[PDB]
Amino acid sequence: GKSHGYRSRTRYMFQRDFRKHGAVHLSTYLKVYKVGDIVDIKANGSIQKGMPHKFYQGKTGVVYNVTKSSVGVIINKMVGNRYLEKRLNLRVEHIKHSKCRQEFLERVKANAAKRAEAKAQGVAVQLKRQPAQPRESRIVSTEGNVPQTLAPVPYETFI
Amino acid sequence: VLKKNPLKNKQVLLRLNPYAKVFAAEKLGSKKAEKTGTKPAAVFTETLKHD
Amino acid sequence: GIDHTSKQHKRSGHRTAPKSDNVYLKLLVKLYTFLARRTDAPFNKVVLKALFLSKINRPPVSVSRIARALKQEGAANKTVVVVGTVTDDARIFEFPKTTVAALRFTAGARAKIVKAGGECITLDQLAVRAPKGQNTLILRGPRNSREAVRHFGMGPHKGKAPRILSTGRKFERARGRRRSKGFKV
Amino acid sequence: PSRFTKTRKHRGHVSAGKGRIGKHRKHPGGRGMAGGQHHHRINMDKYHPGYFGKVGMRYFHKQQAHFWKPVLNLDKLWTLIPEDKRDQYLKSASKETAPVIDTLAAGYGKILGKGRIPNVPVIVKARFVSKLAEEKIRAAGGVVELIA
Amino acid sequence: AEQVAAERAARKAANKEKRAIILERNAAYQKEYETAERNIIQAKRDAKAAGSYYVEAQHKLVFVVRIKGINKIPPKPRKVLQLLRLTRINSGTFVKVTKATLELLKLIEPYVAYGYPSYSTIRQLVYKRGFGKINKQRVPLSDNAIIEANLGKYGILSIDDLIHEIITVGPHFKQANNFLWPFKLSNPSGGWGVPRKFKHFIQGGSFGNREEFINKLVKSMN
Amino acid sequence: AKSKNHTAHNQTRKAHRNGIKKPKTYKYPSLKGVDPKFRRNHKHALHGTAKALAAAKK
Amino acid sequence: AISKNLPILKNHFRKHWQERVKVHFDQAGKKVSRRNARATRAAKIAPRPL
RNA sequence: UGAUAUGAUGCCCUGACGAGUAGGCAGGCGUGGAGGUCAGUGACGAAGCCUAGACCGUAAGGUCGGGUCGAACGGCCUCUA
RNA sequence: GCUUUUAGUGGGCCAUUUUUGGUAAGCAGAACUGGCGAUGCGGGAUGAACCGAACGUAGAGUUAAGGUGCCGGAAUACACG
RNA sequence: AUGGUUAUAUGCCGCCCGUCUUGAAACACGGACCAAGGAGUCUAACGUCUAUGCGAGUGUUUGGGUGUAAAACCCAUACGCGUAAUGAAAGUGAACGUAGGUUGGGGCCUCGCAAGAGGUGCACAAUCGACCGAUCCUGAUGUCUUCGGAUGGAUUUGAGU
């Protein structure tokens, strides 16, 4: 018969990342999670209490409830033709902050500073991001760099 | 009521773009370029006709 | 051969004429289609949309709801406009002097409003008094207080008043409703 | 009328709005409430929770005249004074001339205190009063006289 | 109320000042285009003389023509083709070249043919197949006031203002391009030049980057 | 009388007919399931700062 | 046979109910005949109340 | 919506779109009978029937001519099956 | 953005790619997408699914896939083998 | 004469419909032909929606009065549903407050040429509270000393205010 337990199909997921087994380091227990923090869920295999389901491994949500040895994380789940909001009480060994919000909050301090510096100096701030723009025209010199002529190679076996 | 084409129908070509009247004056699309007598470097020709 | 991004030939989904054949109501739509088109006042585009509404979508406004609306700051002298029916409220014992414009008044609401020296005018006397909607206050009644919207969205753990004829013990109060009989919603 | 009916619109089209595969049959799922615990269970829970089972104790020969006690809130209670005397009694809000309100003859068994009578002293002839209905009636300067 | 010429002469005079502004600005545009092309030619020649290689600037703008019909399209290129406003066969748009659009073009490559349009192709496209999105309702351009009343917030007030905000890709390329209704091009008059359309332009078909030869497509499809 | 067992065919085309929907986040989300010792006090934090702000309009 | 959010109805029509349907068409007729009976009784009982 | 000429469910401008089973909805065509109306048609020929004869409508259908026939029947506004 | 209400449906099948059992099967069963069912048109002579392209009634022009000895519209074209 | 209709000739195309089915022109079923008849109806109780009358009320038509007589017209008292809920029940029973605070919110108001700023914010949506019933805890003044249940609560609960 079929088997669809709570930890089915998780041979390699809750595995403990070769030659980094054993107890976990103490900066996992010293992070400070505030209500609204954006977290990533990566289930520690060695802490069997408070683990998430295998759907939520690698899923990113926000913290809604902060208690003694765990936090409450809000995850959206794709089910049917809608999304539901899921609440997960997971211990802090299976969690870490996102660095993609560290892209944001550091760029907020940069964007707010460049607006103030342009306000005192010559507004037209121009503080949006821009995509990778195409390359400009340039002059490449052949001095010391005379082009070597490369031809296609004949076929050889070499076994 | 009807879309008159520009690039024929010279009146509608003149309604849009009032520069076109003088673009046929100085002719501006059969203008000659100024002749400049610069020659390429030798190394450009050596890498062009190289084997 | 066009890759359509939306449903073709879709209607707007809103009412453009009232479903009624009330000839005096269609004369009120004939008056306010003119005024919404040729005054650019945001008021008249609202009253025209409200004149289309169905009887569910215009709940009755109590006369005590009106007297609460004139207790707003600066609204003591505004003309309160009710697109629908003004009903009497015996639970209020002091009513102010204000003017009310409405589609219908009940015989108790009109008797109360003129008792305090106010005037019960119609929606066309309003449009002669205030074509651009000067000094007005549109009041709407409670839409989600009907009996039918109790049963909307009925399901487990939602608490939405099951459709049932007789009410009390032994009519849907058992297995499925308390933990002592199987499960509880 | 049958003139305005969608059976006049399925003339010409074969299955009369019932489908080719479905083939509208006599009783495909039972008759009436048949199979509420077996094949109609997902409808019984979800829209009718609590249907099956027993709650409470039986009352052999229950008469619903013993339990006749219609309620009247402090919201109205002045509708039981006529309108020609209502404005007369609202003004001169004082004792020694206070309106006796016969709530039983008005058709109520119990007075309840939902809210905010005016500060006129009234005389309430009731059978049953709540706490807060009596407190608000007495805070206006009136009493309640229990009758039968 | 006079109004015979007390306002009519004023309207004629205001249209004359608008038309003088359009005339001098088109002269400025033409001089800028000519100096731009001469300067690229001289940078090429003065790199060849100096013993060097002037690489050109990368092209900032492509023109894309939807080459494949409606049926049998996977959801990701179909969604991208809905986003590039190419909802029917032989329809075209101008696309600003950044990485965020290069990857869209690489996604819908087996269904479109694109390339780098010249000034003359853009000019003939807006002059013959140029339509605007004005409360949407697909209004033909046909007069400079039609462009001015919808794009004067960005400075654009003529048809060469439109072309200049296309070719030189401007600070207001997005609004000027989203104003233009997608070009309902015809089939090519000379044919496609290939027996089989649906392989790459490198393999002798039609789709993909057809770079400067996109003009040879579009001037027959326009 | 054997038959097909399971297929996920057409289920994504079905789910995108009505265009799979986001859960419509709100300002002031629900405090349901939030830690009761925090939630008990937050009643008094809000009530006290309403008393203190209505005191500014005495 | 049980499908929608509809209230559970109790229509007691599983017997042979169609053999015992009494439509009262003679409401007007019995009203007239009853008034005629009262008039005839008031005639027979000529000085007395009904 | 400004009258002194008639459709404001109107008239007019503009743009885009149009496959379709099961199925939904909308606008209509036709039949038996009922209320109102056209002071309607009719033994100088009603209804019916026949007609590679004509007209209108995308269509359901409607109208007219000719023949046959002999006593009743239609248009419109609604009701009903 | 939101809500109510209700129909039909709950036998499916094929194609590219991944893939299981089987010697295999126009075999049995999965995954993703696209189709057929529900769909006409041009091509593959012929064919539910392939290629091209999706359809109101028409006119002109241009093509797609496929073709141009004759049936058959269109080179008994040109070029190297 | 153009044109329309019609028969015929010619070029190209066109497989019997209806049905069940993944698939029917099928070597699947019904159909020789014609005329007439022939199949989602009515009732009791209901769901949503809409229209209408009235509106904290509503419903004349069981019955009575009347009548040009199964029509129409008029009417008392009841009763049904609604205006109170919650508990198995005994029972108890909906304002601390501008009927609350915050976040949006059409419309209105003030300033302005406008862009905009501020005030007020009906409905509606999110939230935190307050009130009523049930469950659990607390048990004040009092007492036929075991009744009474004030006051204060609680990740509880309700088809409520």
Image: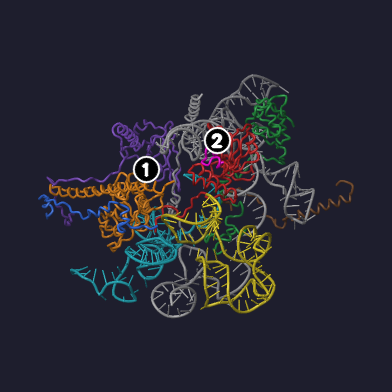
Chain colours: A purple, B blue, C red, D green, E orange, G brown, H yellow, I cyan
Residue G9 appears left or right of A56: right
- Is there CB contact under 8 Å for labels 2 and 1? no
**Disc 1, SS:** loop
Q: Position of residue I20 (x, y in %)?
A: 37, 55
Between residue C140 and residue B8, name the one nearer to us.
B8
**Disc 2, SS:** loop
Q: Which residues are magenta?
A: C126-138
Q: Position of residue E10 (x, y in %)?
A: 37, 46
**Disc 1 residue type?**
Met
Marks 2/1: CA distance?
68 Å
State the residue position of label 1: A13
Residue E165 appears in the figure: no
Asked whether B19 falls inside the magenta stretch, the response is no
Question: Chain ID for label 1?
Answer: A
How packed mark 1 is, by other alpha carbons closer than 10 Å (few <14, some 14-19, many 20 or more), is some
**Disc 2 residue type?**
Lys
State the residue position of label 2: C78
